[PDB]
Image (cartoon, rainbow over all chains, first blue to last red; front, side):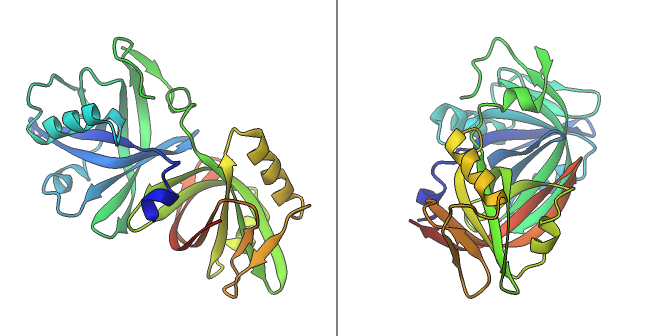
Length: 141
Length: 138
């Protein structure tokens, strides 16, 4: 029912990451969508059981690496690696502490704006401060 | 590796244009909003943007239930035409008013009876996040 109703609306899976006291903290999040283009704001959902999200929510800047569409197996595989201490991935840490996965098409350097509870997860709305595109990576469709 | 805008990277991203409507003291109030997207599935919550200059939105934002009718993808000409009609006193449209006051446009494929959950400032507009309490598919 719910899936069928909103099937026409695709969404992304992303890696959320930051350097905290020189230690990489990262998680995968789903239902990633833009909610405002100008000014740029985006939204994703994080599980309330996440042990990593508490370490990230209050950081000055978070790195959003867009992995792909939610139902893409390759994107889900990257998401799994993100949860696995970034196994086999190259990471880039900006001076702000925001961390990105090299080899992903879209990097959004972001800051949390609002938290909205939603069942077993939390909706996270963020301001986007910088957008970087990798030309060597096929764009998300 | 080159800089970009969210506008550029997410231009071809499908988002909706919707009619938001309610019966207020027996008078129809409605407006069209875009950048409509689901921000959560289970439970369902949705988001759209409304201009801060809107004279209709303040009449709607505090109503117990709003009717969201999804008109189509926001770049589709037929959807834009429905949005225009919505703003032109629902010209040529059939409306359905629930006892709750939520109003829907007949002939649209998805009705979401909704309540405002959060308002997030966004420059010259506002991001409206709503909790969806009833879903109807035509």
